[PDB]
Image 1: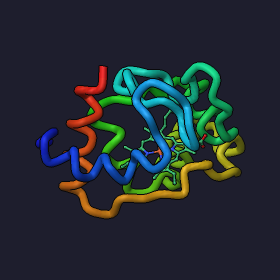
Image 2: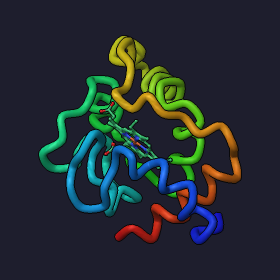
Image 3: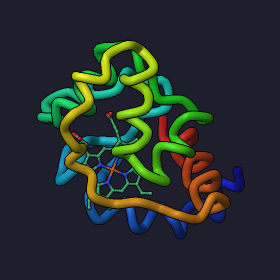
Image 4: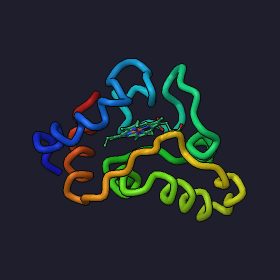
Length: 114
Ligand code: HEC
């Protein structure tokens, strides 16, 4: 949860994400507190879209497990909602971050991206 240390991890995310405009992935400013699949103008996968529709709001706590394995997280979320059929597809985000400390730190960074 060291946002400064998260800066170095965030450089990887900058391959596809910008704070304020969409790119390969959606704009991330204000992602902490945002309903999944709702960045204006971005076309999400059904998996991410359906997760937000089922109520997923990204928080400082749940983005951490998400980054370890985006597909597993979103599939598990929808399955827990009794919506496993809406989780058959995969996310467009083909990146994963195995290290837990790196995930905690980059999510602390995200929380400062207002
Ligand atoms: C390109 C190879 C990517 C990299 C590197 C990272 N992300 Fe990404 N991300 C990408 C796409 C194409 C998408 C849309 C997913 C879909 O299925 O539509 C995403 C999405 C996210 C989200 C969800 C945002 C939302 O509005 O619901 C988050 C929280 C996210 N990405 C975070 C994130 C971070 C912190 C990264 C560096 C650790 C990162 N992504 C890398 C593409 C790519």
